Amino acid sequence: NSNICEVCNKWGRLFCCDTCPRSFHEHCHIPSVEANKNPWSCIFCRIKTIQERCPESQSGHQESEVLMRQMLPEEQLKCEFLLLKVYCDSKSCFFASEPYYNREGSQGPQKPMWLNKVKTSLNEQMYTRVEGFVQDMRLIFHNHKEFYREDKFTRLGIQVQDIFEKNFRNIFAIQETS
Ligand SMILES: [Zn+2]
Ligand SMILES: [Zn+2]
Ligand SMILES: [Zn+2]
């Protein structure tokens, strides 16, 4: 197995996947690495299994259909994995914890949002459809772009949104377009 966490790239107290060489900190994995379970399979492995059981699930889909899906177990897992893919980028640090807004010439967003809040909401089963999760994720970056205006720091929001959107299109097999 790897000797660093797949998500944060640090060593420490790591749990090892039984079906692949990845390793994780307990609360870096999403969901948090389970208490017992021998063998244990990581989220990457569980997602690959879904795909392998239903090869047709990789054919292209319309976003509008994906967003209306109810959060049954497989869609719950897919959103957990998409959230984890965001955390895998080191620039996610800017969006992880609760933000605050005190900048001359800007006003804070009406509905603040952050990764750890989305994480809690998934854990607590607060989303009934994929749309709920995707809306909160996109809100993180939209709030950032609007608050930071012309400051070059707005680019961090563009960068992390691009990670989110590419992973969304991959995980939910969105139909490729120009
Ligand atoms: Zn970690
Ligand atoms: Zn694995
Ligand atoms: Zn099938």
Image (spheres, rainbow, N blue to C red):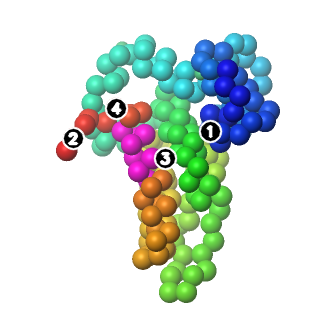
Residues marked 2 and 1 touching at CB (< 8 Å): no
Q: Mark 4 against mark 3, which lies toward the viewer?
A: 4
Where is residue 88 drawn, in percent x and y?
A: 57, 42
Q: Mark 4 against mark 2, which lies toward the viewer?
A: 2
The mark that comes first in sequence, 1 or 4, is 1
- At label 2, the amino acid type is Thr
- At label 1, the amino acid type is Val
Tell whether 117 sits left or right of 172.
right
The mark that comes first in sequence, 4 or 3, is 3
Read off the residue under disc 3: 133
Q: CA distance from mark 1 to mark 4?
A: 22 Å
Read off the residue under disc 1: 7
Q: Which mark is residue 173?
A: 4
Tell whether circle 2 marks a residue whose Cβ is less than 8 angstroms from ligand 3: no
The mark that comes first in sequence, 3 or 2, is 3
What stretch of residues is rendered in magenta?
Answer: 161-169
Crowding at dot 3, Cα within 10 Å, few <14 / some 14-19 / many 20+, comes out as many
Q: Which mark is residue 177?
A: 2
Tell whether circle 1 marks a residue whose Cβ is less than 8 angstroms from ligand 1: yes
Tell whether 79 sits left or right of 116.
left
